[PDB]
Amino acid sequence: VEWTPCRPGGALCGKLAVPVDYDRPDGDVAALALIRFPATGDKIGSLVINPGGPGESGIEAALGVFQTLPKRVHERFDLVGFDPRGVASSRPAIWCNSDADNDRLRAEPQVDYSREGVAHIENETKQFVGRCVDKMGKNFLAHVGTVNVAKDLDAIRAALGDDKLTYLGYSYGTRIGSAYAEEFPQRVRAMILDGAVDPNADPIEAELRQAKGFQDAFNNYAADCAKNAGCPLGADPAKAVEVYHSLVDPLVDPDNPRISRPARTKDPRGLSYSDAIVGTIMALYSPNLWQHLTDGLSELVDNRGDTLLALADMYMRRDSHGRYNNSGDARVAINCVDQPPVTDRDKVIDEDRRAREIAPFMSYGKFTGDAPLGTCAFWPVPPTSQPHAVSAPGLVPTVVVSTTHDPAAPYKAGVDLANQLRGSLLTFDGTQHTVVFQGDSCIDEYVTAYLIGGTTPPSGAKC
Image (cartoon, rainbow, N blue to C red):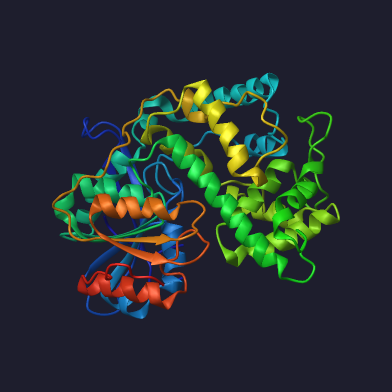
């Protein structure tokens, strides 16, 4: 990789060629984008980070992480972000939906699970898959999966001149981590895994624990808001779910679930039911966003929807010109090859029955007896990984950071990953998804000590 300056730091940029298919070593080729912020002091190596998703840009994440990086880390490490194969600035980039395709889905309330509703959703799904194949070809899609990003990560390690990898992964970046740990355990100098994915989980039970996580975060958000003057969910947090629904339900036509009655916004779209749910979910990733959820709900009281719409736009990555980045398309293409899809209708139907009970804030109306299959049930290329316990006996001690009321990656999944990896579990008491290098000096101190001196937190460490 030959480096060159960028388009906000002392940043350098470059690309790295990797083979699309590691079994056809000089067939089709992909170019991974990389960003590098040079160390200011005595350089141990490169700190490579990944923000998760999947589909989220590691380059953009390095730019954010740069501002909140502790001084000692910035001294001792080159901070490095990369865009995984198929993501953001990497070529070729996964593209399925036009900007108009995405807007058209988001205008639908998406709550009709009658047989006609399910059939409509599954038709939309088939057309999406068709568009992915038409724009990407089956070969590239076959190989965007995590098992191949781990291989790219080793090529990135070498390209950067590091003997052993120093790695921080958030969320899905955790799955990149444990996959790299299994294929290249002798190249791991150090590894922090914040907001963990347990690679051994059943797909459906993990989704239901995730639904429970968001419902618990909602409960926490509502209890907090209940102490505050003018709470749009009312002063009784046991009635918050009902009050929430009195606010979002009218966004759907009560006699015909397929008809949206969007809340008025200054934007021409207005706020559909589905965007109201998505904006709420976005807000529950962090208490930093609870003020916005409160504003957006206050707006709904007046039949207005601007803040919830901007919250959903943040989640979907739609900028102010109506253009989407590719994170949405990429997320799906990657998830669909990372494990066997659930194709059994009865399991999907029963998952829906339970989720309505576990997370009623997310659920509209009553169980109908039907539910749609996920996009992955229709994917034309097969899974290139499968659930299993992480086994990497020779691996250096690692740190798994896990937040007690993390909605997206529940506490217990971090515990289980730490067990499998036989590394240290660092606990953060809070209701947010991830926490490393995001303000908290106690967490950042443990992580700094581990990154430089190799020192792990003691058993039962809390922050």
